[PDB]
Amino acid sequence: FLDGIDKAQEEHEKYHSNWRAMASDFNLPPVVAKEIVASCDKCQLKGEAMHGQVD
Amino acid sequence: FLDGIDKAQEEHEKYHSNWRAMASDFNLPPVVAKEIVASCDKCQLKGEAMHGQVD
Ligand SMILES: [Zn+2]
Ligand SMILES: [Zn+2]
């Protein structure tokens, strides 16, 4: 679990690749690749959330 | 990977337990338990984000 992710985590930092790319790069299920995105605040929170246009 | 999560995912829905509880319940590493939280929008986005107090 942590072994493949350690090498995969570095790849994420280098390009912030999507979980689909990391999954194929290490042939790991989306759960492992998706979790790396969950730890990456930049790829996880993509704006949206709120910040409406104010009333 | 998906087998334990399937049973663990149901437990998450029942109580929205934190990844620490699910990890101990199925004795799985934080990566597997943390990913379930990543899929749960209610436990993932806990307000914050933005929504400042306006100027
Ligand atoms: Zn990223
Ligand atoms: Zn939840």
Image: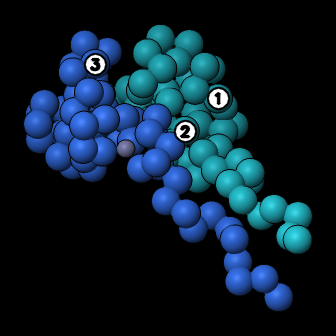
Chain colours: A blue, B cyan
Q: Is residue B12 left or right of residue B46?
A: left
Residue at numbered disc 2? B37
Residue at numbered disc 3? A6
Q: Nearer the viewer, mark 3 or mark 1?
A: 3
Mark positioned earlier in the residue sequence (2 or 1): 1
Relative to B41, does residue B22 appear above or below in the rendering?
above
Q: Residues within 10 Å of mark 3 (few under 14, many from 20)?
A: few
Residue at numbered disc 1? B18
- Chain at numbered mark 3: A
SS type, badge 3:
helix
Could you tell me how far apart the alpha carbons at marks 3 and 1 are, in whole angstroms?
A: 23 Å
What residue is shown at x 62% (from left), y 20% (from top)?
B21
SS type, badge 1:
loop
Could you tell me how far apart the alpha carbons at marks 2 and 3 are, in whole angstroms?
A: 20 Å
Q: Is residue A29 visible?
A: no
Q: Quadrant of the N terminus of chain A?
A: top left
